[PDB]
Amino acid sequence: KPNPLQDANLCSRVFFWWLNPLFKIGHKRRLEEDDMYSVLPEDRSQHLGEELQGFWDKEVLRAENDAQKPSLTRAIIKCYWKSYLVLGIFTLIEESAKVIQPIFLGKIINYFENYDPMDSVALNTAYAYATVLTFCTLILAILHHLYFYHVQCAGMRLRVAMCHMIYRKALRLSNMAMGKTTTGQIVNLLSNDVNKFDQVTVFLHFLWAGPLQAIAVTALLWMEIGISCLAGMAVLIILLPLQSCFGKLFSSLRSKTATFTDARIRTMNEVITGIRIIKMYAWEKSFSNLITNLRKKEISKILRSSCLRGMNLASFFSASKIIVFVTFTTYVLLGSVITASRVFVAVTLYGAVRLTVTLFFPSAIERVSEAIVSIRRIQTFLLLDEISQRNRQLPSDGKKMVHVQDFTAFWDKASETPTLQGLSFTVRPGELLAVVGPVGAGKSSLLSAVLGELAPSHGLVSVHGRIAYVSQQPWVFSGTLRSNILFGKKYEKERYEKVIKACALKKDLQLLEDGDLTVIGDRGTTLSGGQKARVNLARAVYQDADIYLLDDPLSAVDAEVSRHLFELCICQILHEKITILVTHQLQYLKAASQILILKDGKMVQKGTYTEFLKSGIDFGSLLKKGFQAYKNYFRAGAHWIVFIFLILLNTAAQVAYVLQDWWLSYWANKQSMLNTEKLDLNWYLGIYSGLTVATVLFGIARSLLVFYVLVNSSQTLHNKMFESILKAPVLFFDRNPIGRILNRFSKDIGHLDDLLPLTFLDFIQTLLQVVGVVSVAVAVIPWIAIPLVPLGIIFIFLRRYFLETSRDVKRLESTTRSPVFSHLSSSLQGLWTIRAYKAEERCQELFDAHQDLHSEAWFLFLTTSRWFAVRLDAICAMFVIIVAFGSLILAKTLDAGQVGLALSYALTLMGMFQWCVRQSAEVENMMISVERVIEYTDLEKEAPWEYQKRPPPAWPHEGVIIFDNVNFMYSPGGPLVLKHLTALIKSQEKVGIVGRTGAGKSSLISALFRLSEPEGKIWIDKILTTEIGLHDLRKKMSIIPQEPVLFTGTMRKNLDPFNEHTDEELWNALQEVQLKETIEDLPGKMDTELAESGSNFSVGQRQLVCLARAILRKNQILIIDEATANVDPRTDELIQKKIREKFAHCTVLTIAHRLNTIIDSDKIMVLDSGRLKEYDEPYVLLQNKESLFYKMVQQLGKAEAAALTETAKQVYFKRNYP
Ligand SMILES: CCCCC[C@H](O)/C=C/[C@@H]1[C@@H](C/C=C/CCCC(=O)O)[C@H]2CO[C@@H]1C2
């Protein structure tokens, strides 16, 4: 993939003409990783990594030689000054041009000030001055992008070298240091702390060009307007701390919202996750109240933050007006006079020096500080203790053999007992050494010591040969299965097929689409644990080293495949291979040529399996211990009257902005056309101050009103969302995952909270300033309207031709960035496996090949934006050239003031036009959040919570529940679930449910609570369920869910969220479940704040809490589901006895997985694959041997079935015959 940047001219690299081909492909189809362009030879990650590592090693060597701390900053400066000084040389020219061109503006205006149509020499000099002006703008517009590319490329280069060295160091970290750090702290300086280098360079040169330009402009101002300049200049300096006091008060109102936004998101997580429980309990009004309170206390801080942001942006808007106003007020008050040249040169000087002082220099300070902090972090990460490179091997005679003598070691220098105590044993080729020991013996530490991963404290380890190692936890990296097995080794067909067959991988390969070529991501998300272990064993076999270490390989696989692996691979293939095995299955010890027992870190005994049979020590003994979106976004915030007022306020602000400078123009014209006589100063200063004040107030009003309207618009959208999701049926929650629903209320809501109203108040600001500039240039020279139409239309087409490729390349630099982090993560978790093989240098090449794929999409993202900016500045330069020259070919009609106004505004169009375009792109990027928010504000809705026909208060009177021909389906068009359900439930009876998992046992609750409006009829005391709203049907039925959940809050709430009960009632209810005492030893009585799902509570305790809830509701209907999954037997029988003897007179339906729970129930649904077949007393069903109840009783066993039948008979005989 050749790069046209390498074969291009200078005239082609200034206009980025080498990039036209790609754009043409980008206009037709979508862009992939093949349409991409490769990188320069001087940009491959390996090259920069090697160079900067060389300089860093030299610097640390000199630090050792001179006994002071080494600094990475010095290495960076040493490696980059020779190539960073060039950029500085050019930015000096750029700032010099930005300071020079006002003077030639002044010379043109001065030619207009002394107009004489006959003096053609002055006309020619003015044409020359205009030509120099266009040269300045064409070196500020066309040569500033082949500069900005290289300024961003220096940062790209620095970051790529940094990432390469970080990975290189993290590949050889010592376990002493690797344990004190984490694997999240080794990705959080390669994903968030190495990105600063991509930005600091962009502004680095402004730490010396900022002040220099601020002195040059000040000197020019003094030369032209004199001491009064300081006055205005003073105001500009005031903008430096004032900008850093809207930041130490914005960051106190922005980090005081997280303590509310995160609370709101966490409550939303608990609401969305357990929505079945909330709906069944009919509690969602309580969570609605809680989220309303949190969202209101979050909108308060968002409203202060947005008001402050709006005031800051209006200060940015009106700062130039204030500077010019105070400057010329002082200039006139000290006794001088206004002419149209000194005014409109000083204006451009103030514009340039303001754009430098208030915008670029603080950003450079911030970014240099962030880059210095990041450099300090990467300094700390590169001084961690390394691993001793495997040193000079003692001269052997060619005998590949492992011998250990008197080995002692510690994982920590603080541990009292050493991990190993004087181990002195060896192994020879062909001898399958094995280790027997319970967990905690040190067998893993033993293999680590064999690998050298554990530092020897005493003794010696002699390992001479290639080492093949298998970790206890199988480790798979990002790649195909064949590549996973090869692990860099070249493929050999017969050597790859024997591995496959001996590892029994054929089944797994035939299960997947690509056979053995299926791509396996990180953590084995596409594989199973057995597959991971088998692929790791395949890697170990195919690497075919001299020495093999296997730590618990067969534990996680089935018996047959494990036996096959041990026999035909470990016993057969490795019978000629040095092998050390750690095992937990005793069956495989018979084939071990040796056995070592390790305990308390000490050798217990080595010998053959026969000798341990003779020792009398049984092993078990040892092993046991569009446009519509914008309209909907703007309609929500305010009615259209306020929107029309907003438009009028924008127009008034911009018009007053323009008219202040127009007033300076008019003042100059009225002064030149004079005569001693004077000019009435009070009037002129009065209207000039009035225009300045109008500009300031209208800017502030516009900013606050736009922020208020869009914040209100977001507040309304969020409220509509939330109150439209609390009413969505559970089917919607089944279709969409939690993450997608728990992200459109934290990510999407957060984008329209304090992101959307900024790029939308900035975009309007700069769009109206551009329109003001264009309208001034058209009102001064109307003929400009003719050429300016071929500069609108072209622009429009341009903005398409770019946005059909930028959006196709700002996803490539995102979908090819994650592989770097993925490989870094996958290489640290299997790091021992990587370093066990000598091929650690080969993973460096894989990292580079994953980094020469993101430094190849940052290339296109850095050059396509420049191909757009060159043409935008060509359009703006055509505009300024036409304004500067066409004001001279028409010199007979214009005057000094009009020319000054038009030409100075055309000069300030630069950069402003680009920022307008950039914010337009960002708004069109961030309206997707509004689109998603408005997609959820129009979701499905279940039947309303209230109906006209409210039920009688006594209902249910008894509990009679009649299922009449109930046909229920989870989703429309899906499989029938309950089909002609016809049953009767008489008050107070106990009806168990039997069936298969998913055969309709858990759908009766789904249909009886109308979680999905059923077809058929259900009568609760002769009242149709579908004829009453949900909260008059669910409030009168209690339930015990499968997995109890406690909602974050006081224990008062998880029982009485509506405050409808009193402390004595709650205490009594908790006493009935005997957990009363268990609570009155907590910090609070009931007001103990809890964790997620009551993490300080047990599953049985949670079931007790729900049982207490059911007791508190004291309604005459009740449903139990999955009583005790794996709860301890004491709590099991406790719950069971409470289920009977508290709820004797409360009609009970029970859906249980077992029989003892429901053996004594009065009756039983028998559900046959979604069909009710048998329903009577359990003893009657046991009388008929053909009943499914009889069959599933007998399936348990003989004694169990006999006891169950005896219990049923006892119940029958005690009940029906008194
Ligand atoms: C994407 C290209 C942007 C061009 C930047 C241009 O040279 C800026 C000039 C001023 C802009 C302020 C820029 C903001 C700083 C950019 C830094 C950042 O966004 O991280 C807007 C306020 O008046 C004009 C437009």
Image (cartoon, rainbow, N blue to C red):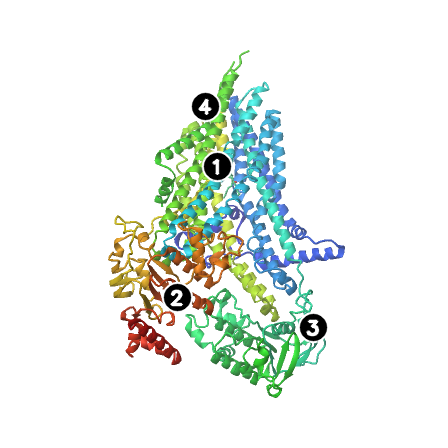
Q: Nearer the viewer, residue 1112 or 1193?
A: 1112
In the rendered structure, find residue 408 and report the number of the disc placed on it: 3
* Measured Cα–Cα span from mark 4 to mark 1: 49 Å
Provide residue 1192's location: percent of width, then percent of height. 34, 76
* Vertical placement of residue 510 versus 670, above or below: below
Q: Amino acid at mark 3?
A: Thr
Give the mark, 3 or 1, whose residue is nearer the N terminus.
Answer: 1
Mark closer to the observer (3, 2): 2
In three-dimensional space, the C-alpha distance between marks 3 and 1, rounded to whole angstroms, equals 67 Å
What secondary structure is marked by label 4?
Answer: loop
Q: Quadrant of residue 228?
A: top right
Question: As displayed, is residue 268 above or below residue 559?
Answer: above
Q: Which is closer to the viewer, label 3 or label 4?
A: 3
Outermost residue, top side: 676
Q: Which residue is labeled 1 in the image?
A: 307
Note whether 267 is above or below 212 in the view shown: below
What is the spatial separation of the Cα atoms under label 3 and label 4, in whole angstroms?
100 Å
Task: Choose mark 1 or mark 2, whichever is in front.
Answer: 2
Is residue 734 toward the left or the right of residue 535 in the image? left
Among the two numbered marks 3 and 2 on one chain, the one whose residue lies closer to the N terminus: 3
Q: Disc 1 or 2, which lies upstream in sequence? A: 1
Q: Secondary structure at mark 2?
A: loop
Q: Callout 4, which amino acid? A: Lys
Q: Is residue 503 visible?
A: yes
At mark 1, the secondary structure is helix
Within 10 Å of disc 3 (Cα), the crowding (few <14, some 14-19, many 20+) is many
Task: Between residue 468 and residue 4, name the one nearer to us.
Answer: 468
Whether pointer 4 and pointer 1 mark residues with C-beta atoms closer than 8 Å, the reply is no
Residue annotated with mark 4 = 892
The residue under label 2 is 1122
The secondary element bearing badge 3 is classed as: strand
